[PDB]
Amino acid sequence: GRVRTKTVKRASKALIERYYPKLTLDFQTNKRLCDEIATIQSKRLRNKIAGYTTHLMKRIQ
Amino acid sequence: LISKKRKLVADGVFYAELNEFFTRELAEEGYSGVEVRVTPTKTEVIIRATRTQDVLGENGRRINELTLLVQKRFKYAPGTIVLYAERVQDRGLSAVAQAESMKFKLLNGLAIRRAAYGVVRYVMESGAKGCEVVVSGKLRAARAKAMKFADGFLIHSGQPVNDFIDT
Amino acid sequence: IKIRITLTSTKVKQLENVSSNIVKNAEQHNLVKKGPVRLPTKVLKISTRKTPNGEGSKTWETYEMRIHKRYIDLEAPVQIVKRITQITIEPGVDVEVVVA
Amino acid sequence: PGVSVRDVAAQDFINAYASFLQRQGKLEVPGYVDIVKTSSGNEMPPQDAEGWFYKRAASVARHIYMRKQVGVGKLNKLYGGAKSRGVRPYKHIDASGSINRKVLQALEKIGIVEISPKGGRRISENGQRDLDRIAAQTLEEDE
Amino acid sequence: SLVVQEQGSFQHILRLLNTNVDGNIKIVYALTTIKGVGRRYSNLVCKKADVDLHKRAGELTQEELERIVQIMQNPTHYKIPAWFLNRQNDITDGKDYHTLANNVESKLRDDLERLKKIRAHRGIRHFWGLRVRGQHTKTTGRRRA
Amino acid sequence: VLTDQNPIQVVVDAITNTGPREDTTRVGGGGAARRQAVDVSPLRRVNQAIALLTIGAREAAFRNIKTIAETLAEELINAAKGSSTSYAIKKKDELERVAKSNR
Amino acid sequence: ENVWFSHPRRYGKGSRQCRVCSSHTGLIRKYGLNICRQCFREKANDIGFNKFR
Amino acid sequence: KKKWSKKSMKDRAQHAVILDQEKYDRILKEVPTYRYVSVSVLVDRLKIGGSLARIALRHLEKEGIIKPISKHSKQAIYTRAT
Amino acid sequence: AVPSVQTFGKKKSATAVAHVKAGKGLIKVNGSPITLVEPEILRFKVYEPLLLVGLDKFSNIDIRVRVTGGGHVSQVYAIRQAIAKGLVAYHQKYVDEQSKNELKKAFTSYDRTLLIADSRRPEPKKFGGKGARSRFQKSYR
RNA sequence: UUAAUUGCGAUAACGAACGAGACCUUAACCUACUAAAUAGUGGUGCUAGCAUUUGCUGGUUAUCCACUUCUUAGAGGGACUAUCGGUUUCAAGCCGAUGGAAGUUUGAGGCAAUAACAGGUCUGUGAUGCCCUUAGACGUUCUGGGCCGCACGCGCGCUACACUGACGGAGCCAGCGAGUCUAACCUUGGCCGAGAGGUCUUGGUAAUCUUGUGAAACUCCGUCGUGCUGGGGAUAGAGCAUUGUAAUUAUUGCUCUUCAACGAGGAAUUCCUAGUAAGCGCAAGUCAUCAGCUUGCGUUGAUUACGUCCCUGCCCUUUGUACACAC
């Protein structure tokens, strides 16, 4: 299953909480921006955090 | 002489033999651990303990005796191995020190409840994020039951438990 | 004189900076040399039963250990075996100086 | 053109070199050709009876051409095979060392394989030219 | 084409070394019926006798069967390896022998009786009927009585 | 060589002529046994057709002088023209008749 | 005396013992460890033997 | 004990091991009518043993009629060449 | 500096490198012509890249392939993948896209395995059975 | 809805912790970086064979030059189900098609919570309380047997029950891993012997030498024939060697001969959804010698589902209970 863990769910909502324009409507452009913003020790974890964030970026539109 | 695979297997056995000898001999000195640093000709074995004054002891005869003791066991040559004595840092976050300390308290006759909860309070007041001690055996009766004293949170699975938790 | 610096250890990070320090001392002055040769890692594996007794479902284990071997090839006269011989040794990794 | 031993199929060349070894038997004929089993794994002697020695010599010489140095143990390992050890499962068993030794020495007598440095044997300078001449023949026989 | 006809010299059955040798099969394998002759020994006997291996037992000229027969009863005289015989270094004399159809079974009883009379371990276990090579018998060798 | 048409055509018409169209299923539910007929999907028809042809030739080649090559050829040719001697055709008759009886 | 230990233990299990407890039966002679398996598990992470897979 | 299995082959109709004359006229006039011929075909219909078809299959292939459509490992497929 | 390109290819554990330089049409594997395979049945399987598009594009190239590892079919699958990637590489350093793009489309239009290697690899064996999924025979009573 | 109290959300509950997940290792990708005769590649010289006409196949460390595609790695990148079209309060998510080396948490493992067994081990421990015992000792040690002994009954396994075969020739390709110092290991090569094996030497403390482990299953030529037979090799007899102080109830290896059951296996039952099953051999562990065992590795590589709780079991909720050592 692709059910996201609460760790990536809560962090992604917190990212959009203070960073509306930073997370662009595309995945690749803001995927590295999430790394520059939050201290993430796993490349896999930040990949999924940006994926949910980008998907949330699309839904809010 | 000795292949690299056998050489590194031997030095780990050398570490295992040296660590257990120090644990059995300097148990009352609050021994924590050892670092075996090897360098050509001379080698240094740094000893970590709380009572470093007693570790060297009486002008340093005991530490010289310990140097002479591992001398004949490991078949070295005069002046090839030197024993050091470094004071242990963050003594409240060393499970080896607390395990030995609990053993002496139990051997003396101190109450198990007071000692077990006393040591765990000392641990987290030193700056830890969690501790847990288990005492099992014949307590208060013949049938053996285990007691668990804990506070805080302790992760149990994954890489980080080996990376972080010392048992 | 064909000085070769052989390094074996079990910790990759500690062996890496020793080679980095050796190679950084090499690229200083002139010291035309050969870089780190990456030998395949020797992975020991002893498989043992978890059960100390004979009772229990068959559950085996594998205690492995990786050895990383890299050698550094130098080429210069005595004016660097007064200098390279100053060992930059960290705990773990070891050095064996071999000439020719 | 540029044909050689590598420009030919295995079966045709070995038979062709066996053909150009039986017509004039210059090489040798050992006294125990009809009693060997070629290995301790094989259960029966070869059914070729009359030949099978120049057939092995043809295969050995062709094997020498593509390589540089081999040994009698190397030939034993190559020419061996699985052995049916009764109810026990099969196991790899080396060939008969004396047979490959006699073939290898026989190839030395004619002048097709000689000893090489770093140990082992090697194709001969006269050996290379005649073996290549065989390839130029077997292709044109079918043509 | 390697096709030849038959005139009537084919005999459907043979009798060599006082035993039945059935025809219709190749000579190398039709001689395996003799008690004491196997695939390798029959191949060796036929090879030195020059009997055209690809020949049926029935389609064999009588002058070649005697040559085969004489090799059976005296192999060592016809350049046969000393290591190609079943009875090597006989306990009675020491000369390399080769037991035949009736000799194979009879000589077998003599050596067991020699083993039995001397009261050796192999002799007594042979009389008992158990294994004599040291096999386990707890779970094997049941349907024997 | 025998039955001179395109062999690929012979293969495809054979499997379409030996694929069962009706089959029975377990419905025992609760009470010893009991069958019940159902239908066969086109994919299962091809799978059953191939399986029947392979097992029939394999069994007919068991302890027999005829090699598997001619046994496969005879089985496919006979099933291609819908003759009763085929093992696969006879098996298709059994399954269809069983399903028809338990309809 | 000369009969106390005259038996030649140099080619079997009786010629080898653990360096920790001198225990017989199962031992680990691989890479010249000469340690029996069950205490090898206890002191596995002292010689550098870890478990990743 | 009990086996719960049968033990019987049939009735071995052993036949020619050496090619005779009364069937030499048979083969030369009967196999040229075989649309498909191989080792097993004349083993069954012509009733020929093991080491005579291989010679007979080599016979006509080298001499005449039937032709190598596909002769290969353990299968010699020949037609009614005419 | 004579025209040349290089490629690689794997099936399960084999490797095959094609040094496709400018030549007169020589396709050799381990010093032997392409017509000498070994399974003698997959000879047309290694003949594949020769025959999907035509031999005219093969008249100005010589593909020399060295293979190591794997079974006989694995070696064959290594050779076909190497020469197929060797053909595109020669078209990927000299010749135009129309030559290459319809070359590189048609190869995958027939089968993706010509360029894309097989991703499946052997799985490690687990204790308790002869294989990964397989387990020893357990019984009661 | 999810593999998952994993999330959407609902809501006398709020905020949390452990497990799961996250994490680590390995297998896949990198023609982008660092490189490298202990890995290779191409080129320049020396040199060989075939054709010589233009070339092909080779050999060659002091002949040198250039490179890292393949070979190994270290630092890194890549994968998040991305997009589109359907389904869903239109949320979690699910399905199909639209890149890829990888779209069943990418595959496979490691780690793995609270509570419990009155589970296994005093024959692992110089960890052990208690009991017995300590000199014709229940200690240690010596010699010879024994753990193998077979009227019989069961559990893991190896050979098969022949033509998709057996046998004899050829082609004949892997990966994991191990290997001697004051010892005697892995042994290359030459010689002797049918073979086992012996002999004189060489290389190696190891990507370097054993080893390209030239393995087997596999394929092509032949022999054979549907024959308890050339299937199958139990059972024995004789001889030749290796290991050890010692082999006798043969350690094992090699040669000849003897050629028995077994013709697809009854009630019942075991494992399995992709390189997986199965067929095939190899390395390592025990080891002076002895694999039909185990742990790993690679080779060939199917059919069959994409579902269910019918059988055997598990989780949550409701319900009933005269059960609590708990059907």
Image (cartoon, coloured by chain):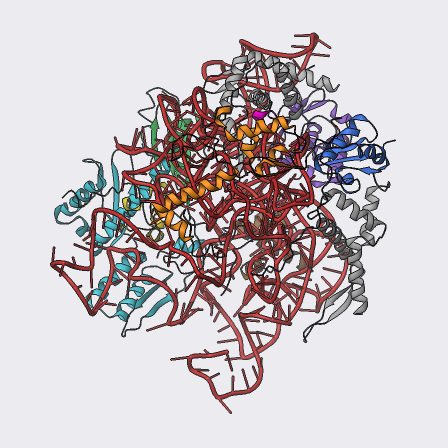
Chain colours: A brown, B cyan, C green, E orange, G yellow, H blue, I purple, J red
State whether residue J289 is above or below residue J157.
Answer: above
State whether residue J319 is above or below residue B7.
Answer: below
Percent across and percent down for residue J108 are 54, 52
Q: Quadrant of the N terminus of chain I?
A: top right
Left or right side of E90 for H72:
right
Q: Residue at the right extreme?
A: H82
Q: Nearer the viewer, residue I13 or B148?
A: I13
Percent across and percent down for residue D66 are 58, 22
State whether residue J52 is above or below residue F87.
Answer: above
Q: Nearer the viewer, residue I15 or C6?
A: I15
Left or right side of F62 for E112:
left
Q: Residue at the front extreme?
A: E18
- Residue A21 in sight in this render: no
In this rendering, the count of numbered labels is: 0
Left or right side of B88 for B65:
left
Percent across and percent down for residue A50 are 59, 53
- Residue E80 in sight in this render: yes
Q: Nearer the viewer, residue C98 or I83?
A: I83
Instruction: Using the rendered view, name the quadrant where residue H27 is placed.
Output: top right
State whether residue J47 is above or below residue J23.
Answer: above
Taking the magenta stretch, the answer to whether it contains residue E47 is: yes
Taking the magenta stretch, the answer to whether it contains residue E22 is: no
Q: Nearer the viewer, residue D24 or G51?
A: D24
Instruction: Using the rendered view, name the quadrant where residue D33 is placed.
Output: top right
Percent across and percent down for residue D84 are 53, 40
State the extent of the magenta-drawn residues as a range: E46-53
Q: Give the residue drawn at x 39%, y 54%.
A: B164
